[PDB]
Length: 139
Length: 76
Image 1 (cartoon, chains in turn blue, orange):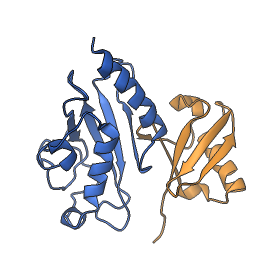
Image 2: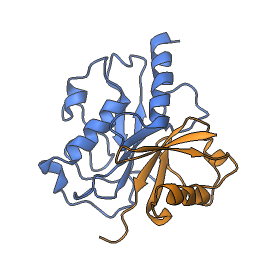
Image 3: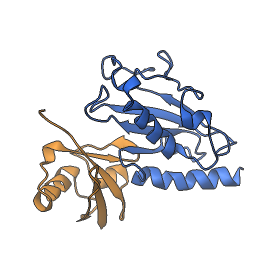
Image 4: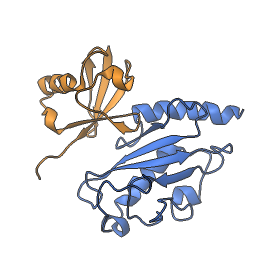
């Protein structure tokens, strides 16, 4: 068992539950029963005055065995029109997101969600026409 | 138990409630001490949205938990 991975994920679980960091971000175990810590859920509260205003976006994060040395798998569940996000799967691209492209072991899921929300406030995304709220890439 | 209700504004208030208490009542208590209308109160925990007609035990909320109070802008 990956001692650092398990230990780190257990710590990030706390930060996710308490929503520490920026404040407008939260995450945690999606299944909850799955203590392997390989199924994380992320929630980003859309910033007001933008096209994501009052839009609660949900994401899915999967931390591999190389975590946190290697970048985890992050994808959107709710339909969102943002640069770097696939329109069919909702999968986020690594080279498109600064923190994913230039990932560091000092990063965390917290930083990822915060960065994504930060990029949502960017001019290139804040004015992107969003599809009907409620539509998901699956189910 | 003492819980920490932190609003997106930054302010963190302490609430003395029991797990058997409903969020609908929790909001009312916040409305009494802070003055924030329950209608525009939206609690976020464990990366998910909480309901009104549910108890703190419904989301497994314990003591010293920093809940997130997201203002639900209604009319603007």
